[PDB]
Image: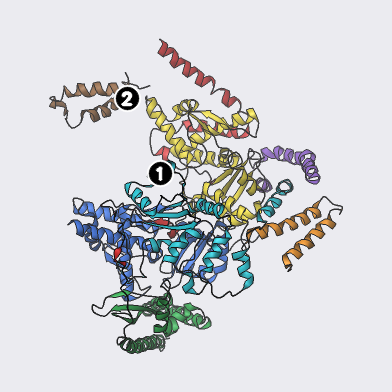
Chain colours: A blue, B yellow, C red, D purple, E cyan, F green, G orange, H brown
Amino acid sequence: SETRTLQKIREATQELLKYGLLEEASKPNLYRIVLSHPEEVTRILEPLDLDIGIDEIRGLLYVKVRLDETPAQDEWAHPLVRRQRLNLEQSLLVAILRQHFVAWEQESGTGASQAQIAIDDLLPQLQIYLGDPGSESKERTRLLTLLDQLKGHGLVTSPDAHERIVIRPIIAHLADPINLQALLAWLREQIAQQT
Amino acid sequence: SETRTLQKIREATQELLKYGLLEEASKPNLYRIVLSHPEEVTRILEPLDLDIGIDEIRGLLYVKVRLDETPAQDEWAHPLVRRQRLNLEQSLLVAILRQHFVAWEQESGTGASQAQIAIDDLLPQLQIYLGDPGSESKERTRLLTLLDQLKGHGLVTSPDAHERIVIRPIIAHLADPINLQALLAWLREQIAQQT
Amino acid sequence: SQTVLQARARSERDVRGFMKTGLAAEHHRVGHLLNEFLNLALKLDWQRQMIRKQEVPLPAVGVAVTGIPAIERLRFKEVDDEAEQTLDLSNHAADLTQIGD
Amino acid sequence: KRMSEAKRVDTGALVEAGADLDDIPVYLQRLQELTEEALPEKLNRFLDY
Amino acid sequence: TLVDALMTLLCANPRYNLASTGGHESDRDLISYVRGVSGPGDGGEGQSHIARPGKTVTGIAATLEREGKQVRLGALLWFDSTSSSVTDMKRLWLFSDNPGQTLEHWLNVYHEGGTRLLRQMEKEAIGLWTYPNKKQYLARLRDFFEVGENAFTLLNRAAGLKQLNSIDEIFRELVLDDHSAFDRAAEVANSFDGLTEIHQ
Amino acid sequence: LNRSSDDGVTQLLSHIEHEVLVIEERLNELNETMFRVDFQPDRYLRLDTKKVVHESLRTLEKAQRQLNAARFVDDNGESHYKALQVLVAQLRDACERNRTLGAKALLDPRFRLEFAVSVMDRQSGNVIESRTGSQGGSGGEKEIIASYVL
Amino acid sequence: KVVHESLRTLEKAQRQLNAARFVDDNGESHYKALQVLVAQLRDACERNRT
Amino acid sequence: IPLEEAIQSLSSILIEHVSQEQYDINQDNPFLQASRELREWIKRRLIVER
C-alpha cells in the first residue's frame, strides 16, 4: 500500500547506525548510494537528532549528534549516544595512533593510503609510558587486546597475518584532539623528570 | 525549507527507542504523546525496519522488527537488534511467568494494577524441570540469574526489597498464540529428532 | 521438630498456591497452549547444559536501539596531577615602564 | 489471511487470540462490541468534546 | 586580554576579541584564556605555545564603587588534569559587597583547600555569595543592578560593533527585552490535547 | 579492444602532476623572496603546501590497476571492457559535475594542494605558528598577517 | 506596523474555523478546521528561530 | 551448621591430615580446599544446604 523507503538506503542507514562508520575503501556501493542521496538520509536521521558529517577528502562518513545551534546547553546530551571515557591505556594508545596518522599525512598528504605499522613497532612506544609488565608475552597480549578493543570503535583494522595494522580515517575526527597531545607530552616530560 | 519533527515527538521516539518499550504506568507524558501520533512514529521508525505496536488495554507501547516487503529473513539477524536470541531455559521461565500473568489477569480483569509474583513461588516451579542441586543458595542464584537475563529483554523488573518481581505486561505479546504454536511445533520436531 | 514442621509449612503453602494457578488457565486459550508446552518440556534432558542452551524460535519484541557509536561521543583519560602547588602570587613589580620610542 | 491482518491492525484487545478458525467467535464478538457499544459511546464523547 | 578578563563576568555568553573581527563573530573561548593558548601552535607535536598545560588555577575580579560602597565581582576556574574539555574545567563564580574579601584572599583559601572550603567560608563570612554555575550568578547580577538580562549582552556587543549594519537587527536582538509569548502559545496548543486523544 | 590502450588517462594524470609541480615551483620563488624580510623581530614568514589526494584519485588509480589486472583474464574480453567502462564512468561523471569540489580535487591542479601560512625562526629555522588562517590573533596582528599574505 | 503573512494566514484560519462551527456532519470538518488552526501554533513554536 | 562456621571447622580439620600424602593432600590454601570439597559433597547428596 504505502510507499517504502528504498531498500539500499534502509540498509545504509541501519549499517551506519550499527557501526557509525562507512568507508569507500570497505563498502563502496553503500558509500556511493549515501552520497548520491544526501538529502534523503539526513531526512531519515533528522527525527532522532542524528545527522551525518561527510568527509569527501578521506572518503568517510560518520554519525554526529545534531543538537541545536548553540542553545543554552553548552554541552550536548543525547539519549542514545552514551558518552564514554577511555581508560588510561586506551587513551595513550589512541594518542600514539593519532600522532602516527598525523605524521604520515604530513608527508604523503591528507587522505593518502595509510602505511601499515607493525605490532612490534608499537610495543616499544607503549613501553615508554607503561614500562615492561613482566614478559614479552604479557605486553603483546595487552597490545593485541587493546587493538581489538579499539577496533570496536572503528579506529583501526584487525592485524594482518604478518602482524601489522592500518589506521582507519575516523581517527581524524576525534572529539577533542588537544587532550591527546597535552596528556602525551605531559607524561613524556614526567618520565624525563623522574629518570 | 528545513522541517523539524515536533520536538515532543522527537523526545518521545528517542526515549522509546532507547528503552525498547514505553508505558503509561511509568512515563505517561510520553506514552500519551506517542499514542496521539502513531502515524508519525511509524513513518519515523519505518526506514530502520522497526515498527510500533500499540496496546491501549494495558498501557503498553513497544517496537518490533519488520519483514514486510523484504520477507523471509530471521528477525534476530536484523542489524540493530542488540541482544541475543532467546534461550530454551529462558523460554521455560517465560512460560511460567505467562501462566502466572494469565491467572492474575483473569482474576483482576485485563487493565490496571501490576501482576506481582513472589520469588518463593518460582523456585518450586523450576525445581521440577531443571533438577534439584540440594542447595537453596545455588538454585536461588540460578533463578536470579535467569530473571536478570530476562530483565535484559524487558519482561520483568529486578527483585525488590520483599523479594517480589513485577511481570511487565509486554510478556503478553512475547508469548501469544501464534508464537506459542510455532514454539510447540519446533519443540515437537526436536523431540522427534531425539527419538 | 520446629524445623521439619517449618519445612512442611513452606512446602504445603507453595503447592496450595501453585494449584490455584493452572485452574484459572485451563480453559483460556494461551493457558491451554502453555500447559501443552510445559507438559512437552518434561521429556527433555535438562541436566545436559547443551540442551538447555538451544535457541527457541520466539520473536523479537521490545528491541532496543542504543549505543549508536558516534565517534564524537568519546572522551579521554583524566590523569591527576599532584606533584606541587603554584602558590606564587608575586606582585610583579617588574612592570616598571621600559618601552620603545 | 484476513484474521492475521486484523490482528496486525488490532490494538491489544485480541492479544489472547490466534489465527486459526477456532478463535473466529472472539473476532465476531469484538466486531459486535464495537458496532453496539464502544463505537457509539466514543463518538458521543468526541462530538460532546 | 584585559577587556575580556573583565567581560567574562558581565555578559552571559560573551563574544571575546569581538572588536578585532569587525563586530559579527568572536574567535576565542574561556579555555584558551585559562590555559593562555598563545596561538595556533606549530601545528605538529609541539606544546610550547600553551602557557599552563598542567593543573592550573585562575581568577578574575572587578571592583565597582559608588559612594564608597564596594561590590567586588569575582570568578575562579581551574583544572585537575591536562584535559582542556569544557566539562572537566571546574568553575566557581563569586559575588560580594564586603571590602575585606579580595581575589588574593580567595586564591590563598583555594590553595588551602578546594571548593568545599570556599563553601564553608560562604557560611562563615557576611556579605559574600558564590554560585557553582553561571546562571544563578547572572540572576544575582540582574537583581543587584536592576536590569533585564539583555543589557549586559548589549554592553558586550557594544565593545566593538562599529558597523550597525541594520538598525532592525540591533533593536530586535540587543536592546529590547524578550517578551515573546511562545510559552503562552505552547500552553494554548496543549489545551486541545484532550480533543486530539479522543478523536484518535 | 586489443588495439585499445590506456595511455589516455595516465597522460592526463601526468599532466596534472606537471601543473601541480609548476605551481609549487612558482611558489618556491615567492618563498625565497619572503626570506629577505622580517615578519617579526627575528621571524621570517613562509608559505607551505600539503598534497590532497582526494578519494576520487584513489578510486581512479584502483580502477586503473584492476584494469591492468583484468586484461589477462579471457572471457571474450568482457571483463576488460567492463573495467574500461567503470574507469571511464568516473571521468564522465566528473565532467558532468565539474562544479562540485569532488571533481575539482581530481581534475583541477589548484585543488591538489592545501596552503598554510607559516612563521619560521630566523636562527634555528623551527616553525612556531603554522597559521592556517587568522582565527584568533589580536587584530593588527590579524592585519599584518592579511597584508603580508595578500 | 508590519503585519507578516503568518498572522494573516492565522487570521484566515480563525475566520474559517469560526464559520465552520455550524456545518452538519459528525464533527469531521469542524475538527479539521480546529486542527489546521492549531498546526500554525505548533509549527511556529518548533521553528521559533525563524 | 552455619556455612561459614562449617568452612572454618572443615578447613581446620583438613590441616591435621596434610601429612597424609597417600591421598595427595596439599598445603596451598586450606580455606579454598574446604570451599571446594564442602560443595563437592553437596553435589554428591551427602550434605544439603538450606
Type of residue at label 1?
Answer: Met
Q: Position of residue A109 (x, y in %)?
A: 35, 75
Q: Residue extending furthest top?
A: C1
Q: Position of residue A1 (x, y in %)?
A: 67, 58
Numbered mark located on residue E121 in the image: 1
* Above-or-below relation of C44 to E24: above
Which type of secondary structure does the marked residue at label 2 adopt?
A: helix
Residue identified by numbered label 2: H42
**Quadrant holding the C terminus of chain A:** bottom left
E157 horizontally vs D13: left or right: left
Please give left or right for residue A146 compared with residue F140 in the image: left
Q: Amino acid at mark 2?
A: Ile
Q: How many marks?
A: 2
- Residue F103 position in % (x across, y down): 47, 80
Q: Which quadrant holds residue F133?
A: bottom left
- Residue B89 seen in the current view: no
